[PDB]
Image (cartoon, helix red, strand yellow):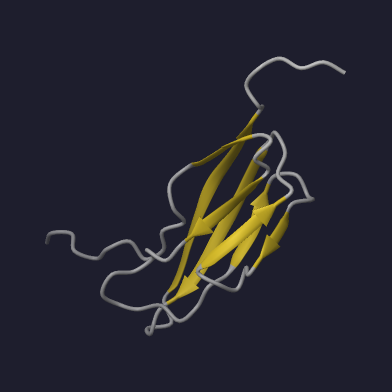
Length: 102
């Protein structure tokens, strides 16, 4: 038949930060449309160990202390039907445009 099931877990689009902006927010409020969600988990699968995740157990998580690198955060949520879904997001960090001295 045709496709109907919508996105189970949406960890938002690609995240691109540019110093000094060393912090971002993973708003996953748009994970479901019809079937509500009663589970939220934010963890860093790949990337350098250091960043600090806040409210990981919430639809909206915050990661501070980001550096020029690649941070992969997987979002594991569940629906009324104990449906196990996963959704990661590529977080790239660029350097603050412009030269520097010191």
